[PDB]
Image: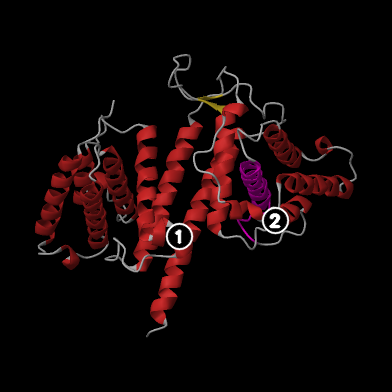
Amino acid sequence: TFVLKEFDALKSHFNDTVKIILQREKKDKIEDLPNPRKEELQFLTAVLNQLEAKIDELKPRSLASYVHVFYGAMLLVCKDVENNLRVMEKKENSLLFTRLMDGMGISDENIPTSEQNIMFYRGLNKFLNFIYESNDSRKGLKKEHFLQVLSLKKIYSLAKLSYEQEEAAENNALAKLTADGKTKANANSFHVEKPIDSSIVEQFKSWDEMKGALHQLILDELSDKNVAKISALSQARSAQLKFLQTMAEQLDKIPNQSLEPSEKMAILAGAMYIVRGQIAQEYGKDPLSNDKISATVIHTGLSTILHANADCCEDKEVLIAAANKFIRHMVIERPEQSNKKITKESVRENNMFSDIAGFQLISVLTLIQNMIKTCRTDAIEACVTKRKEELEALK
């Protein structure tokens, strides 16, 4: 089982790697290297510096979190190297690639687990929020951030790549789950770690009004399609609407003391974004497209209820992530802390969606990962666009 390296071993091995590359290219400074090696090593050096500064500033008792971040950064650079290889050139014959893999202890016989890869890229992606004012991309990039050595285009390219890597890791884990979990879900044991910002769900007015809007949309659909019940719609649309119904009713059963109405609103809003993205895909559009698709009543109505065209990508990510958390709590059984009656993580054989004909649970969780990746990428793109327009308004 793959054991991680210690922080100082990764640091010393990495500085050796810089010396090796510089002597191999006959350059005195990283900045004298050609691209993309220069930007890859500047990135890794900025990450390592920021990690060290945070270690001095915070003096943490454990370094596992920082080790996770650095693993993520080094694997990200490895992916960048693979993306910049010449045709026929193998990654195992790149000095930087093999030096990074060697420094992490990764070989064909010793590879990290899926959970470890997910920790790597999740840690790195959280770490990269340090470039935002108050760690919130709504406020834009910091005037001085720890990746200032890189160009805006490179910052965007690397952040985008990292979000894609977390997406791919999460999806890989999802594809290896099995649907043989025997335990019973407990909605009343679901709790949010951080309460949602109430302003985000204020746009939806109230829980009763969200349920009412969904109901009027379903009545509109049934009347437009000349049918009496959701089950007379197509398999895809029937499954989508029953998915929304099931979410809303399951949330309705939970007492407010255990899950406040604002949280229910966030979860149902995320679910609506999921259905909206599925339909958009039926039209060959990106799940989060803001195009009007006049031919579909459900996509148009959900877009209206969500205020999707006017809402920022960060709010969308928060709502979709809220739905993700609730769905996973309801359909994924995982080993308990006080218990030993569960061995591995799996999908419950009987969960709240089991009676929905043709429902594709894994496809929904994968779509969630895609939309979260798109939200993060939209955030960074908006920030670098804004900074670029600020620095162009002085030339």
* Image spot of residue 123 (x, y percent): 36, 44
Residue at the top extreme? 341
The image shows residue 255, relative to residue 127, as above or below, that is above
Question: Mark 1 touching mark 2, by CB under 8 A?
Answer: no
Q: Amino acid at mark 2?
A: Ser
- How crowded pointer 1 is (Cα within 10 Å; few <14, some 14-19, many 20+) is rated as many
- How crowded pointer 2 is (Cα within 10 Å; few <14, some 14-19, many 20+) is rated as many
Q: Could you say which disc has been placed on residue 393 in the image?
A: none
Which region is colored magenta? 261-290
* Image spot of residue 263 (x, y percent): 61, 42
* Image spot of residue 152 (x, y percent): 36, 67
Q: Could you say which disc has been placed on residue 303 in the image?
A: 2
Q: What's the residue at 39%, 65% (across, down)?
A: 141
Depth order, front residue of 208/112: 208
The tag earlier along the polypeptide, 1 or 2, is 1
Q: Is residue 272 magenta?
A: yes
The image shows residue 30, relative to residue 228, as above or below, that is below
Q: Secondary structure at mark 1?
A: helix
Work out how far the residue at label 1 is from the one at label 2, CA to CA, in angstroms: 24 Å
The image shows residue 338, relative to residue 357, as above or below, that is above
> What main secondary structure does the magenta stretch of the protein show?
helix
Q: Could you say which disc has been placed on residue 137 in the image?
A: 1
Q: Nearer the viewer, mark 1 or mark 2?
A: 1
